[PDB]
Length: 49
Length: 49
Length: 56
Image (cartoon, rainbow over all chains, first blue to last red; front, top):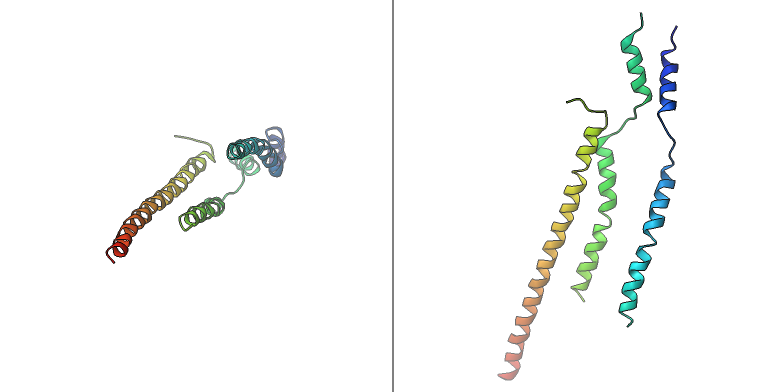
């Protein structure tokens, strides 16, 4: 009386992680939005000299 | 009398999602086609000044 | 040639973005060739304009 649908849900749990979409998307921006403030600052500081 | 071909179709169902091609392709465009209307608007507004 | 269940859709999508982005570059090219049309027009119009003052 193999529980076909208990082995499956035990293969899954051992070959799957957990991921929050809106947390991997907030870090990415966080790091690319720090290099874009130094690119702007540079440009702005040349037109003021 | 293991139903070889019932366990398979139970491993699949637990490690597979569902995806509509023409819905992941309509959103993408939808977001990239809003930034391209602000790039054009900018250019157009400089040649009119 | 056997493949996993999601690879064929990653390969179709990586050529949708490319055609969309290569589509934008075209739009912008055509705009910049319209600036050189406005510019030429302007110049030749200022010349034809001065003529009409001086000969008067």
